[PDB]
Image (cartoon, rainbow, N blue to C red):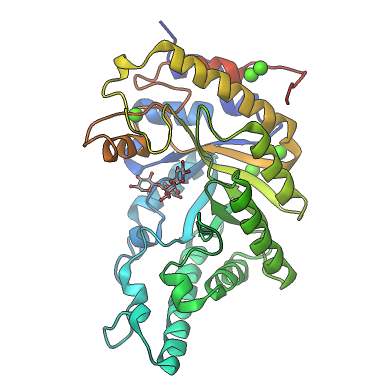
Length: 358
Ligand SMILES: O[C@@H]1[C@@H](O)[C@H](O[C@@H]2CO[C@@H](O)[C@H](O)[C@H]2O)OC[C@H]1O
Ligand SMILES: O[C@@H]1[C@@H](O)[C@H](O[C@@H]2CO[C@@H](O)[C@H](O)[C@H]2O)OC[C@H]1O
Ligand SMILES: [Ca+2]
Ligand SMILES: [Ca+2]
Ligand SMILES: [Ca+2]
Ligand SMILES: [Ca+2]
Ligand SMILES: [Ca+2]
């Protein structure tokens, strides 16, 4: 029987000279064992949902600050670094942003002059959303996910409502506005998943390089790192981090979780007791290799955040259920559903000096 997470050496202390160790949280998790584990193992937080655009401003001028405020207060009280997730996204974004003042959907507008006005209105709404949020939290946030998931998996820019209405201008204006109100001190990140996939890595690199060349203030790349036991390779992860470091950008691992399954997560286990020990062992072997790579690149990585605390709360449960007729669980962390350490904990808390790789 494994010890509980509050009985073992701190992850954040183990990596304190190398990078932050963070967790995504909900306000209701800021009590009990989850809070105890947070304060022991992590020195950085991010809001899993409470700071997304639809959570904060679900209707225009309706500001829903309570959940986000509780996360900020917890970070203040326990002296934790705080990432802000996220200022601009095509999901969990309220639809009122994209409706003109006559009630019509901007994406449907055919008149060229009205499309140009819609672009100005949407950009101004985004500017005011950013200004309001940054002005409230600027003294508590260290790293900002300014834009999230703007690159398409099929190549090129994601053709969300943001892109259809403004082109790339929403990206430039979002960073410019975050810098304007957060100051030069604020660290501004573009965040995405599958940044290890070479075609997507290259699209992101080319977008960021072009923006940097226009003076857009981008400080780093957020690698969501929603990964698997068999994918992506350490080699492709290394190549991605190094490509963005070559532009002078910081790298953060922002939403790390390692699913037991492939994509999509078909054939999921429906009970934690059904998970074979050798799968958790394969997961431990992979986390070992992953965190050794992070150690090798520690000069280029400021922070590594897991998208959750322990296996009893992870969006990967919902993904399993979406692809297995409503049932299924996933177990992606180093702490299991009972808060007991997993094989993976032991394989990332130890200290190795000779890092092997391909
Ligand atoms: O909506 C996004 C998902 O589509 C994304 O899912 C990824 C799709 O590409 C696959 O290769 C990945 O395995 C899978 O995780 O996750 C992020 C979410 O915001
Ligand atoms: O509770 C769920 C969240 O955990 C989930 O968080 C998103 C996962 O995909 C990533 O690509 C996003 O950046 C991240 O915000 O969003 C859905 C929600 O139901
Ligand atoms: Ca830091
Ligand atoms: Ca090792
Ligand atoms: Ca570092
Ligand atoms: Ca789970
Ligand atoms: Ca190790």
